[PDB]
Image (cartoon, rainbow, N blue to C red):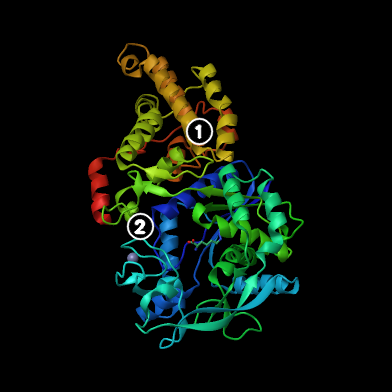
Amino acid sequence: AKKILVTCASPYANGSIHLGHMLEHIQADVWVRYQRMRGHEVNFICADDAHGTPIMLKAQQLGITPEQMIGEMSQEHQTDFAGFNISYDNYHSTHSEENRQLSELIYSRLKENGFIKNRTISQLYDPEKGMFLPDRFVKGTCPKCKSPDQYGDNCEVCGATYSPTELIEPKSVVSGATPVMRDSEHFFFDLPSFSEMLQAWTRSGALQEQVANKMQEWFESGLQQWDISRDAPYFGFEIPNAPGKYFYVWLDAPIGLMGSFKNLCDKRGDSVSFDEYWKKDSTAELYHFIGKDIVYFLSLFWPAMLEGSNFRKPSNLFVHGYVTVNGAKMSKSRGTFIKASTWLNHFDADSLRYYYTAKLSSRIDDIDLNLEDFVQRVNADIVNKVVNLASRNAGFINKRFDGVLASELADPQLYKTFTDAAEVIGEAWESREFGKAVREIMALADLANRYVDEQAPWVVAKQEGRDADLQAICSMGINLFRVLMTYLKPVLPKLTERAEAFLNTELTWDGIQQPLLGHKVNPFKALYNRIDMRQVEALVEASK
Ligand SMILES: [N-]=[N+]=NCCCC[C@H](N)C(=O)O
Ligand SMILES: [Zn+2]
């Protein structure tokens, strides 16, 4: 009955999707699929973050227009996300007419309300290329240790940090020319004006404890005005009434989510939903799944921008940690910096979705993909606990009972124990306590397999006149499988489709209250095969 708009952080167009991105998109998708299972109106929205100096320069290097380049990466990204079954209702681009209009609208409202300031700043400028240089596009000699070819505000030899203006014999990374300081008028968003409102939100109790504590650190350090303009040449949106000035990519990026929803509504011919979700009086819920590295933008700048332009603010922010492989940050040299596209050449999407989900929680802690554990856990939980309930019982049903399940539950009490768990498991999915949900589900899977072992179908099957007993036992196991797969439906989309084909029924949350009785099931190839370390080693080698 609820109206829910869920988003993920837009990936930058100048890089491929990797395991880090996947943690976020998978976490959001699991939540979204669960919400849909409970009957809510859900809109899962995302887009590609396509603006900025890095993108402009990359396109020039490739000898193609930025439009062509971002279009190609947009397609690559969507192909990868589709491969992992991330169920977006719309995947748009920050480089769109919807975002241009909404960005200009919000800026205009902020300006009229007195939240935009004008001030001149001094910045390194490449006189040959003819452009201001972001810090990472300036290189030179470290002022401290004198090591050459250091980039930006830090030295990778002695570890010193400094303003790029301190670099000795500075050189433009773009042209090799010596940059010089040049003045430029910039537009600033008055974030400080929203301090009280933001502090009230922080203490409201909606945000994760860890996020709130971090925000207090930021309030203590003090909020500052935000530089939201960038000089031409730039790939982005030009600022109205300010020739040669553009909106900094980060200003238009989150607005791109609004743009993506507007685009969806417009394509659907829906003239009412945009305002219903974004106006101040909205009764719809808005959630953003994001990583801790961008919390400053989404928890401070964003709500302030919306407030200042008369739009509703986020209902909540769901923050996740970093993804590590084998306990450490992804390493290219070790072949642990894994691309989403590469992953799919070796393993299926469900395996990673399951592993991440088993480790995820409502906190911001990092999630570790230990490859040895990945093999053991997938084989133990998916193949040996859940799918086992179907694979060890389906054969007898198809071969000896024409594929027809028993007319009654052999153990109603046990079945009730399984359906009684729906409340706690659903609450776990709802609260994003994924690890807890999986633990509950697997504990039930253990009970199901214990039941089968107690009945010993491999013994009953060889004994005279025990046909009825065999059908009863095997049918009971299949019904327990039906329940478990329902609880796991948000997690394993593909295995779920195969399970639904086998069971000849769509799995719904409430449907578990009615077991499958005197019901025909279909034969199946192999619902889920085992994986091994040889495959893991191949994945790593292919990633080097
Ligand atoms: N959520 N949200 N708003 C926009 C997020 C933009 C994310 C950015 N492209 C990044 O990769 O850090
Ligand atoms: Zn140094």
Q: Tell me: residue 456, above or below residue 250.
A: above
Q: CA distance from mark 1 to mark 2?
A: 29 Å
Q: Residues within 10 Å of mark 2 (few under 14, many from 20)?
A: some
Query: Looking at mark 1, is its residue's CB closer than 8 Å to ligand 1?
Result: no
At which x and y percent is residue 492? 45, 42
The residue singled out by tag 1 in the image is 436
At which x and y percent is residue 413? 54, 17
Picture quadrant of residue 184: bottom right
Q: Residues within 10 Å of mark 1 (few under 14, many from 20)?
A: many
Residue found at x 75% / y 58%: 280
* Residue sticking out furthest to the right: 281
Query: Do we see residue 3 in this rendering?
Result: yes
Query: Looking at mark 2, is its residue's CB closer than 8 Å to ligand 1?
Result: no
At which x and y percent is residue 472? 44, 19
* Residue sticking out furthest to the bottom: 128
Residue found at x 55% / y 67%: 250
Q: Quadrant of ligand 2?
A: bottom left
Secondary structure, mark 2, is helix
Q: Viewer-proximal residue, 398 or 543?
A: 543
Picture quadrant of residue 247: bottom right
Secondary structure, mark 1, is helix
Q: Viewer-proximal residue, 443 or 114?
A: 114
The residue singled out by tag 2 in the image is 341
